[PDB]
Image (cartoon, rainbow over all chains, first blue to last red; front, side):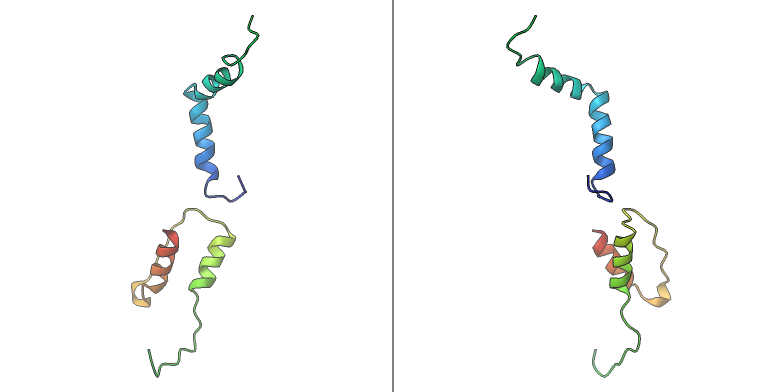
Amino acid sequence: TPKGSSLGTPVNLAVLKLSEQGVLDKLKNKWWYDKGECGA
Amino acid sequence: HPFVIQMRPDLKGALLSLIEYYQWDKFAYLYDSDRGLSTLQAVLDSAA
């Protein structure tokens, strides 16, 4: 965020909120190892 | 208002510009009623 943004702190809080809710991990798996064409 | 010459300038814009310079997002406003609520109106509207 541009420093001094009105969006900075809620966006940050949202990021760690998503991290704790397992959202970020789920998304990582969704785009990395779910759409993965070579799994083993 | 006509026939009134206010020697004193308008401070509202300077206060708002200053709040924007310090880049505050939240603050406390202690206003004197006997002075008029005009600046209060300015900072409230610029708050919204």
